[PDB]
Image (tube, rainbow, N blue to C red; front, side, top):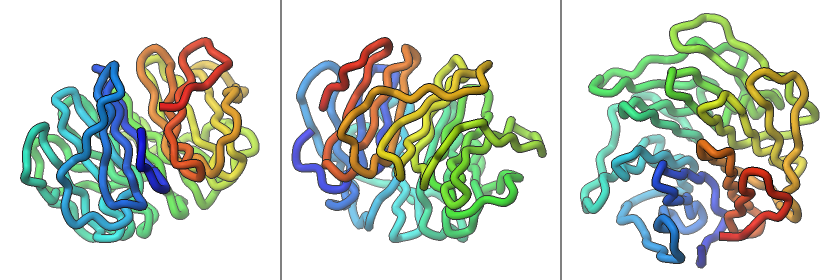
Length: 251
């Protein structure tokens, strides 16, 4: 990537294309799968965009944090769509599944809202006790993980459940992004400690990834191989740690 300023959200598709919220420049930039081909999405009127999510079809959703809305752009389209969410305040994270259901962390209202594919009326997920939540992630089942940023914790809600689970991460400080793979492993950007941590689905003690020189990292995204992308927000770059490596690369 080039020309990023304070990048925040990152999303990766199954084809391996990478989208980043070039938050300081009110735009979304894209790095095509398997090359150094950068393009810039034709979003208009964004203000401090935070999160970004993408589906298999190349449709991109962005949380327009300053304008309290979520905007969608289909691949190759010049027309953005404002989703029928209501009552949002400074929304942060967004995640989508393969059906086009959209989950948004409604940060200012300490809640996560959902727009089921095909529906036009949001539901509020029954999380409780959230404070200034940020990242959100979903798996193919609709299990939702939210970074409960104000409480230094990550919380999981299975779909349709009224039981939320606090994940046993250790030493988190103002965490930001969260990402999950098909194996149930959970990665979290520990923004306050300049590191990324991970918890496997059947483990109780986190692993710390050997990233180095991160500054206020924000977004994180993962693929099915366990390769991780992090927005190194303070250094205007996106870093990548492949599965099984101790040497990060810079996109």
